[PDB]
Amino acid sequence: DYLRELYKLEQQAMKLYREASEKARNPEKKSVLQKILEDEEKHIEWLETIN
Amino acid sequence: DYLRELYKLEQQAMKLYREASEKARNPEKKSVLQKILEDEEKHIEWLETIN
Ligand SMILES: [Mn+2]
Ligand SMILES: [Mn+2]
Image (cartoon, rainbow over all chains, first blue to last red; front, top):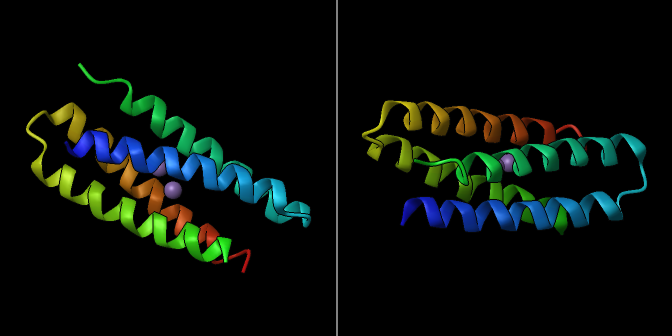
């Protein structure tokens, strides 16, 4: 349950951060968003790492 | 509105990660959940720098 809802939310985050990073024009902002996006992708990977 | 939705999502994630960390009976997995929770807190901090 918890893990699945977390996975769902991480997927939502990846989608939103990708879109946001693509809409951003200020390179510093784009960079911050891409950095967070990488983190969420990492979380997704980490969640797929269980038992 | 996208930054706002990102913030909302980060809070949802933080909620669920704290709950999951409190319910975790496997120490390794608990450790990972805590690391992720900290990352999300960091993401909120980073989001405040691009508003
Ligand atoms: Mn995450
Ligand atoms: Mn996050």
